[PDB]
């Protein structure tokens, strides 16, 4: 079965054969599309075919499919599974798997970078202090004084689900949120629940609008522990506008390194519940979502007042007008401080080229339109006009429940 | 099987039961979502008829009444006898309103119950069709105070007697391809503009030439007609701050009147069913004016604003896009032609969604189409989870007549 996608701006038509190699389900049925739904302990029984599928992929990629090295590896894994109920990936396999997880990430516009990913193998880690050390090294390497480098740090895989390694932070670097008795929120509202946990675990909160949260680290199924990332290692950028001089007086800044820490990485049936990764920001993640979402810093009103827009009717598009200037400021600030960032035009254009290349060399590129299209200026980016097929390949990054909902407290 | 949708900006969760009534297919499977793809007989007829009549009769609180049963029997007899059946006026109106109500891609559906339906099933000729359309256009335009309306021509019979409006909208600007290699007018309408000329239209070869109607009655060859200019309301586009903007020489028409869709009610097919409401600002300012395969005016506007078009990261395109959209809204409002901004309209749709979930058990919605083509996440719809599914009666797409017409 062949599937065609059309760009309605260029008339380019592409043919997907890659979806045929798809296992995991979508949420959709022939009777319903769930494409805008946000989120729609394993026996040796189901483990070997998953191992086999991965290893077959891996050996095809290195042009060794059916080799004695291929076969002996399958054999080796099969035995280790029946002997131990799990298995260990070679370093080469771990690296290949991590990259491909990113490559298969249908919601990620940044995938043109997928082959350049520094893999830090942290599978010898045993303690939270151990995890901290690893994470610090990740942040320093990835930050590279503003010349950002994509990296992932991979802690030991799940075993019985009772000894999980987890990073409790959703991102390695993120700002605290504090609920005030008057109902208002100080700092990042998205992080209120987590901030409370930290406080309850002993964190002494500065209680400001941009307090970098402590790391909360769980090793081997033990209770999590608090560590403060060395400030010298947290690269931040003050936000100013190139023409508006009052913009600095808004008091805004952001951190340079987006480093997602709460996902689960799946490689050949193996589950890596602690696998923080980092790249660099697309400008709109901050300028549109973090700053302008109503449930986030929500700065549109204050910006619009200072610009003196007509705020009495929405039909003045005062919101659209202010949203742009904020995004201009984010981009300007980062570039001025020589910290890696990409605008939504450059990133979407690069994605189209990537996606086209993937169709030619790979027979497809699964992609989630709802997530790929930027949260401002949608149709003036080329992805808006691009038909996309969404399906799930392995290796993959998966969501997992927040650890505080599941963690068995040792006390 | 009972599905919940969450708004992530408000945490509000709605439960969907309505989707269980879904009949048509989506194009999606458990293995692949096609959410972003633009277009994924007697024994066939009576179940369709019955399903429709069941819901019609349920809506007026006479489900399982004799008048219900009797109607079912009447239509059932009529299908057996005639191989088709005719809709009562009451049913035709309910059906059209519900087709709109079920249009999962329409953000304006809060207005769905207020639809003027023009029964044009007695129409036999293209001149006849022309008369009906002029009447429709004039009613709907209402001197700039737009009223929603649909005009319904006779239903399909044997597919060889189809009524068709060849235009995609009742009102649209012509597209001419230049020896210069560029495109004059609306590039989306180039092919249709040729077919007009192929049929004898005398093009003024301008940039904003209102296209002639190309009307097909009873399967016959289509005829050309010029909508009386006095009936075509247009708006010159000026900026409330930039004087030079008027010099760009842009205008647009006030009446969005989609004419190429197929209306299906109780199994019956209405292949000529032009309908109209009013514009959301982004339709003209973002898509019509700023799409690359359209009027594509960004560069020219940006120049006039003197923005740094050197690097993408000055967001000059974004800046212009805003201003262009401000001007469209400003122009329509100043002239008192009905228009809605993307903020007002999406907020309205959230309310409508709430109503539909509360009173009907849900509301099919296509997030990809509902979210406006600019400023997406500063509108409430962006943060709104939606379930897309197909309910009937419905508006469907259908092939362009020239690819089908046995001349
Ligand atoms: C290097 C520059 C990168 C850029 C500019 C980029 C850009 C983005 C953006 C804008 C999103 C949307 C996320 C949101 O809006 O919440 C995203 C999603 C995602 N990215 Fe990338 N990314 C980059 C690198 C990476 C790397 C290194 C990985 C993993 C190794 C990755 C994996 C993912 C995944 C799994 C998602 C989906 C997240 C979710 O479902 O919540 N990306 N990316
Ligand atoms: C009265 C105010 C209305 C507003 C503001 C409105 C708004 C919109 C918008 C923005 C779209 C997206 C289409 C595009 O971007 O090309 C749309 C689609 C659609 N509308 Fe509405 N509309 C209105 C009235 C109506 C009426 C009266 C009908 C039919 C009786 C209707 C039926 C539809 C259908 C079937 C679609 C999807 C068609 C397609 O897939 O191309 N709308 N509407
Ligand atoms: N620049 C980058 C690179 C990679 C990224 C990976 C993930 C994310 C953020 N994911 C958003 C999840 C937020 C959420 C909220 C509620 C329910 N599900 C998810 C950003 C990245 N940015
Ligand atoms: N304001 C309104 C109201 C109703 C509308 C109904 C339809 C449309 C536009 N339809 C766009 C179809 C575009 C297309 C192009 C190529 C292939 N298939 C579809 C606007 C409305 N606006
Ligand atoms: C309901 C909807 O799926 C939700 O708002 C999505 C839409 N698209 C998105 N796209 C990106 N890149 N990031 C997001 O958080 C979201 N949120
Ligand atoms: C590829 C994608 O489906 C296509 O660009 C869609 C996206 N969303 C849209 N949304 C609306 N309202 N109108 C459109 O024409 C489109 N086009
Ligand atoms: Zn789907």
Image (tube, coloured by chain):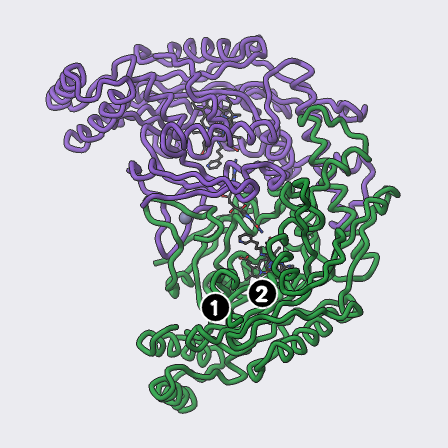
Chain colours: A green, B purple
Task: Determine if marks 1 and 2 fall on one subunit.
Answer: yes
Crowd rating for badge 1 (residues with CA inside 10 Å; few <14, some 14–19, many 20+):
few
Q: CA distance from mark 1 to mark 2?
A: 14 Å
Q: Is residue B229 above or below residue B15?
A: above
Q: Position of residue A138 (x, y in %)?
A: 68, 74
- The residue tagged 2 is A168
In the drawing, does residue B390 fall left or right of residue A270?
Answer: left
Tell me which residue sits at (49%, 21%) in the image. Answer: B257
Tell me which residue sits at (56%, 30%) in the image. Answer: B347
Q: Position of residue A289 (x, y in %)?
A: 65, 47
Q: Position of residue B361 (x, y in %)?
A: 36, 33
Q: Chain of mark 2?
A: A
Tell me which residue sits at (48%, 20%) in the image. Answer: B276
Report helix, strand or loop for mark 2. Answer: loop
In the drawing, does residue A294 fall left or right of residue B319?
Answer: left
Q: Is residue A234 visible?
A: yes
Q: Nearer the viewer, residue A284 or B27?
A: A284
- The residue tagged 1 is A408
Q: Position of residue B388 (x, y in %)?
A: 41, 40
Residue A187 numbered tag: none
Quarter occupied by the N terminus of chain A: bottom left
Q: Nearer the viewer, residue A223 or B324?
A: A223
Q: Is residue A19 above or below residue B315?
A: below
N-terminal label among 1 and 2: 2
Q: Is residue B366 above or below residue A351?
A: above
Q: In the picture, residue B241 is in which quadrant?
A: top right
Crowd rating for badge 2 (residues with CA inside 10 Å; few <14, some 14–19, many 20+):
many
Q: How many marks?
A: 2
């Amino acid at each position: 079965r062949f599937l065609k996608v059309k760009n309605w701006e260029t008339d380019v038509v592409l043919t997907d054969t890659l979806h045929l190699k798809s296992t995991l389900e979508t949420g959709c049925t022939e009777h319903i599309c769930m494409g805008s739904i946000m989120l729609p302990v394993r026996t040796k029984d189901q483990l070997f075919p998953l191992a086999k599928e991965f290893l077959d992929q891996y050996y095809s990629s290195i042009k060794r499919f059916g080799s004695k090295a291929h076969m002996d590896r399958l054999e080796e894994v099969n035995k280790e599974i029946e002997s131990t109920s799990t298995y260990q990936l070679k370093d080469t396999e771990l690296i290949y798997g991590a990259k491909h997880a990113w490559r298969n990430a249908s919601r990620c516009v940044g995938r043109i970078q997928w082959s350049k990913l520094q893999v830090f193998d942290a599978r010898d880690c045993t303690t939270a202090h151990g995890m901290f050390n690893y994470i610090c090294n990740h942040v320093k390497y990835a930050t590279n004084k503003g010349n950002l480098r994509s990296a992932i740090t991979i802690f030991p895989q799940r075993t019985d689900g009772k000894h999980d390694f987890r990073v409790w932070n959703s991102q390695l670097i993120r700002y605290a949120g504090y609920k005030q008795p008057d109902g208002s929120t100080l700092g990042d509202p998205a992080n209120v629940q987590f901030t409370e946990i930290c406080i309850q675990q002993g964190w002494k909160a500065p209680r400001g609008r941009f307090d970098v949260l402590p790391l909360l680290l769980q090793a081997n199924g033990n209770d999590p522990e608090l560590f403060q990332i060395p400030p010298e290692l947290v690269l931040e950028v003050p936000i100013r506008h190139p023409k508006f001089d009052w913009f600095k007086d808004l008091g805004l800044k952001w951190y340079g390194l987006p480093a997602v820490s709460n996902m689960l990485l799946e490689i050949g049936g193996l589950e890596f519940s602690a696998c923080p990764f980092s790249g660099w920001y697309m400008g709109t993640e901050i300028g549109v979502r973090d700053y302008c979402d109503n449930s986030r810093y929500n700065i549109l009103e204050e910006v619009a007042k200072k610009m003196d827009l007509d705020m009495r009717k929405t039909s003045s598009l005062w919101k659209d007008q202010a949203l742009v200037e904020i995004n201009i400021a984010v981009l300007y600030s980062f570039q001025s401080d020589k910290v890696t960032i990409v605008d939504h035009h450059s990133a979407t254009e690069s994605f189209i080229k990537h996606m086209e290349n993937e169709y030619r060399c790979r027979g497809g590129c699964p992609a989630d339109w709802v997530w790929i299209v930027p949260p401002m200026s949608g149709s003036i980016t080329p992805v808006f006009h691009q038909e996309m097929l969404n399906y799930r390949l392995t290796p993959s990054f998966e969501y997992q429940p927040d650890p505080w909902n599941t963690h068995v407290w040792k006390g």
